[PDB]
Length: 93
DNA sequence: GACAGGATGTG
DNA sequence: CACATCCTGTC
Image (tube, rainbow, N blue to C red; front, side):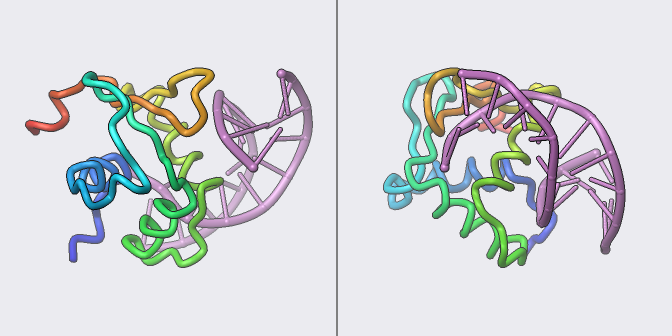
């Protein structure tokens, strides 16, 4: 219902349901996560925001904007792996 | 292709 | 603001 949802909140919600482990999962105990099925998560993000043409190219650009915002960072050298900068703070928020 | 980040546009 | 879209470049 809430269409104001942000990408990081949405990704947090996906990682919270173990039934989504197939496409996105935690890869550390400190906030690192991997987009196992990147195009699949991008598809879900588009449906959520009603942007039918959403894909990883664009979902990843949205994640790149987080770097300076200190919300999410890239885990260098690790394909599709990013990290929530302030974890678990963002969780209990 | 994945990834970085600038340019322009939208609500 | 918070992306969505498109693009130049690197590797």
